Length: 49
Length: 48
Image (spheres, each protein chain N blue to C red):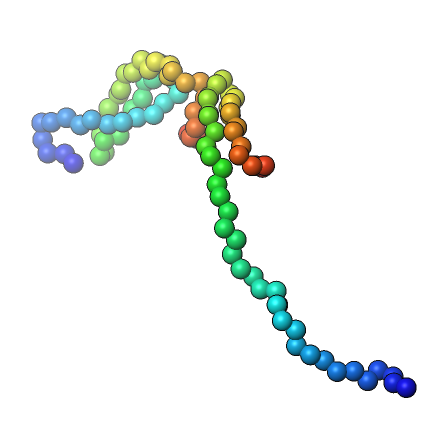
């Protein structure tokens, strides 16, 4: 939900360490800069994309 | 002095499908590793 001059918090999943991705909110796009770090576990108990 | 002359009688104790009650093995001590799983199995009776 949007109104006017505000902000929004979103949860995202990625595999890359250096992630430069575009998020399409409604009909307009925004560039996101992220420097993701490695997790503590090497083997996981659920599948992913 | 008899060919195939015979009679027939109904018999007790017939076979019927019922339900058996069993138990479930106890959880094993599980420890995770690099692409491997370790299980410490403690069976009370022969468990598959």
